[PDB]
Image: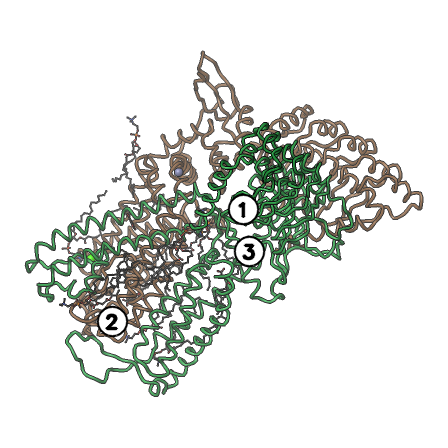
Chain colours: A green, B brown
Amino acid sequence: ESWAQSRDEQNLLQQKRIWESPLLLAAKDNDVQALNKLLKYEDCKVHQRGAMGETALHIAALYDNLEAAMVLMEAAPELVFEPMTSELYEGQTALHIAVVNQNMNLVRALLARRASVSARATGTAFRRSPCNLIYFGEHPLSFAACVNSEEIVRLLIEHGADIRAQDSLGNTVLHILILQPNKTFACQMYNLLLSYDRHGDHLQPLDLVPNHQGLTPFKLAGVEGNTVMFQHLMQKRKHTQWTYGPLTSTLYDLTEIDSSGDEQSLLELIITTKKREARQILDQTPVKELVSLKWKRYGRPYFCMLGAIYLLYIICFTMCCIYRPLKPRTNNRTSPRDNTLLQQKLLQEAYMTPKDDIRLVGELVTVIGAIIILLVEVPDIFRMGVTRFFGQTILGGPFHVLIITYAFMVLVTMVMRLISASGEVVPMSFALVLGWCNVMYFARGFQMLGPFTIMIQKMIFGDLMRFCWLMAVVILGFASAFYIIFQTEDPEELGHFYDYPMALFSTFELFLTIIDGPANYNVDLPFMYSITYAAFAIIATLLMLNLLIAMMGDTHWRVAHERDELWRAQIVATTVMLERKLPRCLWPRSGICGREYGLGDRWFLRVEDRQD
Amino acid sequence: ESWAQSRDEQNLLQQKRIWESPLLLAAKDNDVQALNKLLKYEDCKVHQRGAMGETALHIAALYDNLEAAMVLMEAAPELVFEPMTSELYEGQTALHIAVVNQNMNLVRALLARRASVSARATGTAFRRSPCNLIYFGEHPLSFAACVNSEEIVRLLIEHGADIRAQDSLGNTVLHILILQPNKTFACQMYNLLLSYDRHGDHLQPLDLVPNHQGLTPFKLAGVEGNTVMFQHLMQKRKHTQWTYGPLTSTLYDLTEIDSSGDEQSLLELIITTKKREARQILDQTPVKELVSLKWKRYGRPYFCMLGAIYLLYIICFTMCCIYRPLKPRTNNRTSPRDNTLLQQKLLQEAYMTPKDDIRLVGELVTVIGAIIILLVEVPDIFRMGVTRFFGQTILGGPFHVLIITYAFMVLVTMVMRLISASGEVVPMSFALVLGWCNVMYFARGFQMLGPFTIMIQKMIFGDLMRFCWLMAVVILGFASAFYIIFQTEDPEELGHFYDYPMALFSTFELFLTIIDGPANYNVDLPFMYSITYAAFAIIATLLMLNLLIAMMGDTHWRVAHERDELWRAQIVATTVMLERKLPRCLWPRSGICGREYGLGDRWFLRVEDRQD
Ligand SMILES: CCCCCCCC/C=C/CCCCCCCC(=O)O[C@@H](COC(=O)CCCCCCCCCCCCCCC)COP(=O)([O-])OCC[N+](C)(C)C
Ligand SMILES: CCCCCCCC/C=C/CCCCCCCC(=O)O[C@@H](COC(=O)CCCCCCCCCCCCCCC)COP(=O)([O-])OCC[N+](C)(C)C
Ligand SMILES: CCCCCCCC/C=C\CCCCCCCC(=O)O[C@@H](COC(=O)CCCCCCCCCCCCCCC)COP(=O)([O-])OCC[N+](C)(C)C
Ligand SMILES: CCCCCCCC/C=C\CCCCCCCC(=O)O[C@@H](COC(=O)CCCCCCCCCCCCCCC)COP(=O)([O-])OCC[N+](C)(C)C
Ligand SMILES: CCCCCCCC/C=C\CCCCCCCC(=O)O[C@@H](COC(=O)CCCCCCCCCCCCCCC)COP(=O)([O-])OCC[N+](C)(C)C
Ligand SMILES: CCCCCCCC/C=C\CCCCCCCC(=O)O[C@@H](COC(=O)CCCCCCCCCCCCCCC)COP(=O)([O-])OCC[N+](C)(C)C
Ligand SMILES: CCCCCCCC/C=C\CCCCCCCC(=O)O[C@@H](COC(=O)CCCCCCCCCCCCCCC)COP(=O)([O-])OCC[N+](C)(C)C
Ligand SMILES: CC(C)CCC[C@@H](C)[C@H]1CC[C@@H]2[C@H]3CC=C4C[C@H](OC(=O)CCC(=O)O)CC[C@]4(C)[C@@H]3CC[C@@]21C
Ligand SMILES: CC(C)CCC[C@@H](C)[C@H]1CC[C@@H]2[C@H]3CC=C4C[C@H](OC(=O)CCC(=O)O)CC[C@]4(C)[C@@H]3CC[C@@]21C
Ligand SMILES: CC(C)CCC[C@@H](C)[C@H]1CC[C@@H]2[C@H]3CC=C4C[C@H](OC(=O)CCC(=O)O)CC[C@]4(C)[C@@H]3CC[C@@]21C
Ligand SMILES: CC(C)CCC[C@@H](C)[C@H]1CC[C@@H]2[C@H]3CC=C4C[C@H](OC(=O)CCC(=O)O)CC[C@]4(C)[C@@H]3CC[C@@]21C
Ligand SMILES: CC(C)CCC[C@@H](C)[C@H]1CC[C@@H]2[C@H]3CC=C4C[C@H](OC(=O)CCC(=O)O)CC[C@]4(C)[C@@H]3CC[C@@]21C
Ligand SMILES: O=c1c(-c2ccc(O)cc2)coc2cc(O)cc(O)c12
Ligand SMILES: [Ca+2]
Ligand SMILES: [Zn+2]
């Protein structure tokens, strides 16, 4: 916005000041004879500051003018130690520019005059940001690795580059290559930089050194969805046991992958990333066999056991609403439109028989069970929802909004029972619907979990809610029309639209065709009704048929074209929740440990397969 | 389960005890220097057993080490006569391991030291099981044939390996090649092992030796759907008569294919197996014209006659239920909600007029026709498939269950008629519905109805069982809400939810939109009715749209491309059933008997075809 306008004016007044200054211009235009005349005129203003604090060496390096960049050196050798001074390109020297532009003959002549290989481009354009378009690090050795130039990397380290150097984000030169868009070229540069880590006394192998978020180069490849570097780093963690003809028993490490409770694991960090490429890591041969192992053995059976206890809680709540205390009414019927026969009992007369004491036991099971919902989930939606992730699990999305809304409605029914307020049917009727609609979500884990089952259910609900916005204006147009047509008529003969909230609810029902069209045949209806309702019935039929076709066309686009899994991240983030809630004695750790088989303290997973 | 927990701990215990013992380690690492050290120290415990009861010679053959394996054999040659004595790898010798690993120079080393080529590896990890990735037999000829090694098969026969050795479930080496995943490589090995059957004095040749289930290799390729080896084994059963340009008159054997009437044939095995590529053999040439021969000539006439006799029998049963004996009621009505006017007559009253004697003939035809159902179908589910194929063949046809359940309901109605019990309308109502829905069975015998009935009848138990559970959750949740909203109201105006079972039935009907939404308009309905029913109608719309989208994917797309294949497989199961039940005087045996043409007592089918 205001900042994007600021970058654009900054680049235009850069080119404006390179044209209105001759030594900046000849460095750009590679006018080698124009340098000799101006520099012999008593070295005029060789300490230039252009738009981005640039000197004339920065211009000559930027446009790959090797012949013009030489003349600046013998004229004043103090320009090779000069950075750019603006906020956007802060700290960038000429050695950074020639490395990114891959100018071989220039970068030797810079090192020939002792250019610092440990400079730090701290500017706002050299920071990881979606507004920035490249993130190449902060060091010249980091710039050489990202543009894929093997010969510069061998040249820079020879002059003393530090491969252990880190950024302001803590990323070393091996963290940055995982962030690069071309994966295959970054895979060759990874093997190169590890070969120069001879260094057996640095107390840490360099591909274990964490950034300021604690992530290793292994975990960062799992978070950023870099599947090419993930499979490359996994051969460091395999161990082939035997090969019996076509069979092979491979043993995987599972130290930085499986959860230990005290530390965030790779399975959790894929979920909170919310990226589309990070879910491809869940398809990989150590991780894919781990998720299906614990969602077959502990994760799924405990999911169905918690849903069976919730079903007994809602049945116990349902019985207390059916047998709610009611007495015949005390006052007389006011209007002839008053249908009410019964009313609620007061608190003193609610409990005076032994059959009410059986109900009182059931009413206390409900309230105690409603507090437990608040005591375990008011932490959860703070932890889960706004901090890490929301709506990408099974039992997920509008489950946690609704079951919190359930337990709120039960405690409202308790208050209205105590102060003997009228209208407890209103918090109960919400709580029956809210409570039983949550049972449909536990029914989602009774499935074999295909790749396009839960996301299609989530999709169809998403299109129906978009259809309800477009049909609200169609109802409001025709309900207002139907209201003023029958506004001069007698509602004893046709009372579908007798006041305006009823006319709105009738037109909603006629749209879905769940009540019949109004007709009497013993009296003359207005003529404007018949042509309006014939227009309404054609519109409502076509809009309901186009809804079905639009759900078919949107189903095809997300199965055949969007090509996103969604089905492994749902069973991961469900299994993470049940593992933090249950104690350790009910949850054995997946894999098998060492010290009785002699491999360490590490929890290995054996995978046996057939090559064919 | 705990089976993989016990299996994975032994593979780590194996690698542990290799790492513990110096003799097992240096043989594993092919460190033959320590092999000479540990033998000249002492003739030690060189008959020690690790995890899976193995020796140092088993390890050296497992990890493909020529040099380490030799040193064990000159030191102590008695290790070659040693099987693994655990339960997982019981019976396996080092000769088995070298063959599977295809270490050809090690095979010469063992056979020069007279390694027994008839050892039977009868372990747990060698049986045919869905938990095993391999089923290679129990013999070294069987192990060599399944890894596609010609030079080892030639080497083992020359050293006296029995080519007709059998597993402990019956299979010879010719059976095992059909059970292999690579069909093309098995065909070359099949031709090779018959080229060593020169020594025929054995009454059954190798391609005519049954296993413990009676199946030959030709029938086993039929059951397993091995269409590659089926066509190759059909070349042995052909007989080409003449070639007249592009024409060819091939004569087929039909001994193991056609129903012999004593043994289960090839047609009977393919129908009674739960496989899909086995059904593809119904399009192979000698079977395809055999099936069309039986149906066009004797199957379709006997099926249309049986469909016409059943149709008249149900019309006779229908008129006996319409004219069932009823008299006016004796007592007076109790409540004004009592709607009953008539009740049943008794046996003394039900047969007094000549119209009752006409009905008595029709009732006896009904009872006799239900006993004949229980005599041709009940001694078919007790001898053949005692309780198993009574449930196993239901995927082929559910109409066995419906016609037996019909035949009981007629006899339940008979017993109640004799003891004058009340409530004959309950067993009749099941019998009328089950009587007329069994007419839909005979729709398969028509080309106009057959393929279209396949698409209509095809319902999916993965999504409709999901729909029935979620429908029941909405109905129990919203009928409970609708019950307590109208619990205080007058039910003579709106009586849809007057007690709780009717509210369950009204909400069921409103979900399917088969009764109108409740409305009076002459009285004030409660406010929570409009909120709940609008929420209910959007949920009921969504669950229908979830059901249509579920019916448009990956199963109905499969049936829409396979309905001609699925209909021609119902023709086979109908024809095979009719050929068993009808006597041999009404069903002539197919093909042409070659007794009067000099061909043996075999029944030949003649097929003329154009190669062009
Ligand atoms: C009847 C009308 C009144 C209701 C109006 C308000 C209702 C909402 C309407 C809002 C406006 C209409 C727009 C459609 C909905 C959002 C768009 C969307 O993405 O759809 C998503 C629906 O949502 C889900 O099923 C997943 C859960 C995430 C969202 C949380 C819902 C809020 C809970 C409160 C809910 C109400 C309970 C409040 C009362 C207690 C799914 O779309 P998708 O992308 O195809 O799915 C792929 C999943 N993926 C994204 C992970 C890849
Ligand atoms: C999430 C997807 C769905 C979208 C949600 C919204 C869906 C729609 C939900 C609607 C909820 C209810 C809204 C109106 C309720 C007022 C009724 C009332 O009190 O009537 C009173 C009158 O006063 C009126 O009639 C005022 C209504 C006129 C304007 C309608 C409001 C526009 C909705 C804003 C949003 C629309 C935009 C949404 C689309 C962009 C009483 O009238 P009476 O008793 O008949 O007597 C009159 C006296 N007389 C006899 C002299 C005549
Ligand atoms: C696993 C799920 C699969 C599905 C299987 C489901 C399982 C089986 C499901 C249901 C069981 C069988 C049906 C129940 C019928 C009750 C008996 C009856 O007919 O009513 C009789 C009495 O009954 C009452 O009055 C009940 C009063 C409220 C009881 C609340 C539950 C108490 C449970 C305690 C804790 C539970 C622990 C739960 C938490 C762990 C007759 O009553 P009335 O004379 O007609 O009316 C007057 C009553 N009034 C005076 C109060 C108004
Ligand atoms: C004691 C507490 C329980 C503890 C149990 C401990 C062990 C539990 C362990 C495992 C439990 C589950 C194992 C069953 C086998 C899996 C098959 C399956 O999932 O069906 C199908 C899903 O369809 C469904 O949605 C559900 C089908 C079953 C009906 C309802 C189940 C019970 C509901 C409540 C009744 C009362 C039960 C609760 C009582 C209150 C499979 O679908 P699909 O074929 O993959 O379709 C893919 C098609 N596509 C590829 C095109 C997309
Ligand atoms: C191919 C498909 C199309 C062709 C289908 C056939 C053609 C169309 C089908 C039917 C024709 C149309 C209706 C029938 C005649 C009209 C009604 C009538 O006159 O009946 C009269 C009574 O008569 C009776 O009581 C009927 C007895 C019922 C059982 C019939 C036994 C048949 C015996 C043969 C066994 C067959 C062996 C089966 C072999 C497997 C009516 O008299 P009423 O005034 O109503 O008084 C009733 C008093 N009562 C209640 C005391 C009785
Ligand atoms: C009393 C006399 C009645 C008739 C006799 C009894 C009927 C028998 C009729 C036919 C025999 C069997 C039919 C299925 C064919 C073989 C499958 C099988 O055997 O297993 C089935 C057992 O079946 C059941 O458990 C009950 C069926 C429930 C149907 C629910 C919807 C229909 C409702 C309509 C009526 C509404 C009721 C409302 C009325 C109040 C289910 O197993 P599966 O799902 O195939 O296995 C899962 C693996 N899969 C996912 C890969 C597929
Ligand atoms: C109803 C009266 C009762 C009388 C009882 C007395 C017993 C005897 C009664 C009939 C004897 C039938 C056997 C002989 C004829 C069959 C063989 C045949 O020729 O094939 C014919 C088809 O078949 C037919 O069109 C005839 C069907 C007869 C009625 C059967 C009703 C089925 C009832 C079940 C309801 C099912 C629906 C269920 C849906 C829910 C046609 O053959 P084609 O292909 O044209 O041949 C090529 C000829 N061409 C070369 C010249 C072209
Ligand atoms: C004034 C009226 C419109 C009441 C307003 C409340 C409704 C807008 C919301 C509240 C929560 C309900 C929901 C309750 C649970 C269901 C199941 C559904 O998830 C499933 O399990 C079905 C599969 C699928 O989503 O397609 C998602 C939302 C739905 C239909 C409901 C959508 C609409 C409801 C009635
Ligand atoms: C599903 C598509 C076709 C429409 C989606 C719009 C709904 C989200 C809204 C707008 C129309 C409905 C409304 C229509 C009018 C009624 C009036 C109602 O108040 C009364 O019933 C008073 C009746 C009287 O005074 O006689 C409150 C909300 C309600 C049920 C509805 C609430 C929600 C609905 C379902
Ligand atoms: C006196 C008794 C009858 C009280 C009711 C039983 C409660 C002790 C339990 C069983 C039903 C509830 C559960 C209902 C559902 C949730 C979700 C949870 O599953 C997940 O964490 C995954 C959610 C997701 O992946 O989106 C399992 C337990 C929890 C919080 C609840 C924990 C405790 C509750 C209140
Ligand atoms: C006294 C007389 C006039 C009554 C006539 C009796 C027939 C109406 C019934 C009695 C027993 C027979 C039935 C008995 C069993 C068979 C197999 C068939 O069983 C199946 O459903 C096959 C299922 C499958 O293959 O998938 C159903 C009807 C049929 C041909 C028969 C149809 C008609 C028959 C001759
Ligand atoms: C359990 C899941 C896997 C499938 C369940 C679906 C159906 C088998 C159920 C759903 C709700 C229905 C029931 C809902 C309530 C009714 C009441 C009915 O009659 C009464 O009890 C009294 C009615 C009256 O008062 O007149 C008996 C069964 C019925 C139709 C239904 C029987 C079967 C239905 C279709
Ligand atoms: O059920 C249908 C049908 C339908 C289904 C089967 C038929 O035989 C006819 C119409 C058409 O459009 C819809 C459109 C919808 O929005 C919702 C629906 O449930 C349907
Ligand atoms: Ca109607
Ligand atoms: Zn497409």
Q: Is residue A332 left or right of residue A405?
A: left
Q: Which residue is mark 2?
A: B526
Helix, strand or loop under label 2? loop
Quadrant of res A426: bottom left
| Marker disc for residue A280 | 1
The residue indicated by pointer 3 is A295
Q: Is mark 2 within 8 Å of ligand 9?
A: no
Name the quadrant of the N terminus of chain B. bottom right
Asked if residue A145 can be seen in this view, the reply is: no
Count residues near mark 1 (Cα–Cα under 10 Å), then give few for <14, some for 14-19, many for 20+. many
Check the image and report above or below for A330 versus A14: below
- Residues at circles 3 and 1 in contact by the CB criterion of under 8 Å: no
- Taking the image as shown, residue A526 lies to the left or right of residue A167, namely left
Image spot of residue A175 (x, y percent): 63, 47
Residue under the image location 37 percent in, 61 percent down: B472
Label 1 secondary element: helix
Q: Neighbour class for label 3 at 10 Å: few (<14), some, many (≥20)? A: some
Q: Quadrant of residue B556?
A: top left
Same chain shared by disc 3 and disc 1: yes
Q: Amino acid at mark 1?
A: Gln
**Quadrant in the picture for the C terminus of chain B:** top left
Q: Select label 3 or label 1 by which is in front.
A: 1
Amino acid found under the numbered disc labelled 3: Trp
Q: Chain of mark 3?
A: A
User: Extreme top residue here?
Assistant: B245
Ranked by sequence position, the earlier of labels 3 and 1 is 1
Q: Chain of mark 1?
A: A
Residue B34 against residue B539 in the figure, above or below:
above
Closest to the observer, B163 or B417 = B163
Mark 1 touching mark 2, by CB under 8 A?
Answer: no
